[PDB]
Picture (cartoon, rainbow, N blue to C red):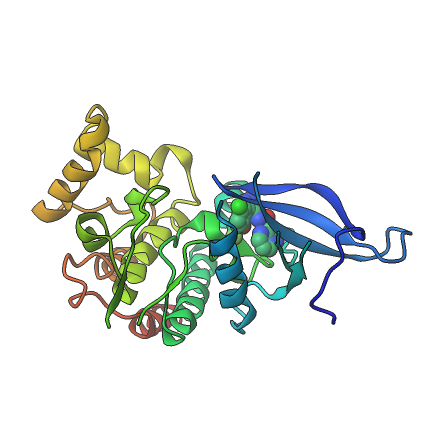
Amino acid sequence: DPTHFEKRFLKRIRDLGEGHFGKVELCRYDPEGDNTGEQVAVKSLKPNHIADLKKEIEILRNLYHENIVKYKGICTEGIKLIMEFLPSGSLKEYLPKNKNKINLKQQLKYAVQICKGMDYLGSRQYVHRDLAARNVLVESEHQVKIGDFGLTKAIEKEYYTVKDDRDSPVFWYAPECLMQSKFYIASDVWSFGVTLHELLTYCDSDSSPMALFLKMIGPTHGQMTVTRLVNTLKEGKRLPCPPNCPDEVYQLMRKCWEFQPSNRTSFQNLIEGFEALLK
Ligand SMILES: O=C(Nc1cn[nH]c1-c1cc(Cl)ccc1OC(F)F)c1cnn2cccnc12
């Protein structure tokens, strides 16, 4: 079985990225021992979320799309997710160091690719729930792929109701996710608009969606922050236009943030939107 990897040949090279429960490392699957094996990205849990990883491994295994990271296999006894290695890392890490390389045309092409990969996920009846630049991987200067699926859940129904909301990226969530933990495909459209903002800002730390919202709502509200974040979304207040971003790209972003899940555009429609701007 080429999808079965033995632990003894999986040679850790370095750490790539880290979440709260999950960890991604660069490894070389080296059966020959001469350090000639292929490099792979390995997802393991930090030392119980074993059940969610197993489900995530099964979601990824059956996802086949050029804008979604390729599943390569597993490593058992207790499981590790084996995927292809994308050396340019995430958009969160890649964009600040490549401003000279990536221009608006390229940013909008990335925008399409994320949309396409997201629209394939939704058509397979899945909600992502963690769509941010940190979960988007860079293949090259021309191609991006959705790199993580840790929060991904199957919609039965227009939505799936979440029980555990503890590591939720609240500054990327739609008001229904914040108010009732209700996740629709439109919730992923809302998160796309936030991911779009990061992308057009080259993922700048000082103008991150969290920081732009803390300046909007007030940074000293502690545990009242989500309520006040919902308060400002209700008022009609949204993330500001990114510097040097044309108003029509900002208009496509504003359509991702229509308070009502039904008033929001679909990914198919966003694809058409950016395609008209690329001609
Ligand atoms: O560089 C990579 N990963 C990375 C960089 N920083 N943080 C992460 C990361 C961390 C976690 Cl816990 C989960 C997903 C992550 O990547 C994300 F961007 F999708 C990488 C490269 N190929 N590859 C394939 C699959 C997964 N990761 C990688």
